[PDB]
Length: 251
Ligand code: HEC
Image (cartoon, rainbow, N blue to C red; front, side, top):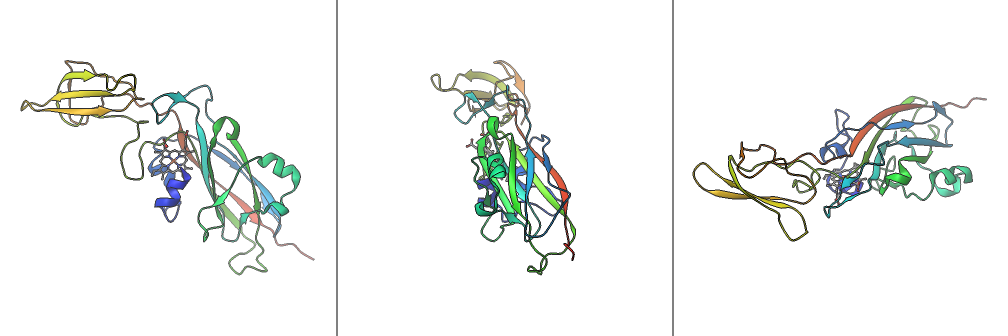
């Protein structure tokens, strides 16, 4: 979630350009973003983003069942650019923005916006109203061709802030040995217990949450860290970059 980014990363974009959502949303899926080629200072314009995905395909949810995918994103604009305040947003654009609450990444990064989680079915494509700065009143800005970076995600991540795997990812054998037991963990609550008999005779019990399916059977020999399940992830995070020229009005 964007909140996870904000809570554990001071800056969403790293030196090499990767967005930190990618440290947890481990699958890549294209995204798109479009802004006008140029804009006059102190004027509102639109950033149209798209986080496409097959809406017919459901994902593994935290509770183990299957369900809809939700979306979120992080937008990195040049210093001085910001979310346009409502009073500056023309009605027809508000219409297209809909019911979304773009928030600044932090109070000190108003040029960095985020939104999500929100339903992917409804917000697969979003519009963001941006107010351009004015080089005249802001010494940190000039009449340049500026880059804009975007990170769009749809679907649950593979690992939490603590570094533990979510149930929406691949599970692996903790040790090498013979699977002498696969117990349908909990009563209709999902998950399994896979007992691996190590070569020394010790049995360790791997806990598999409900969601991913098993690809191993009783009596099967697995190598250390060998996969015991499929990869249930159907979502993904994508990055796109664009640019806009801050025009120098003239008279
Ligand atoms: C690891 C610390 C994460 C970072 C950094 C980001 N996300 Fe994440 N996200 C993560 C997990 C483990 C999950 C599942 C959480 C749960 O309660 O089950 C999520 C989920 C989302 C969602 C919801 C997706 C859905 O329900 O289909 C969204 C839309 C999402 N994440 C977006 C997102 C964005 C844009 C981020 C970058 C700024 C981001 N996440 C970072 C783990 C982590």
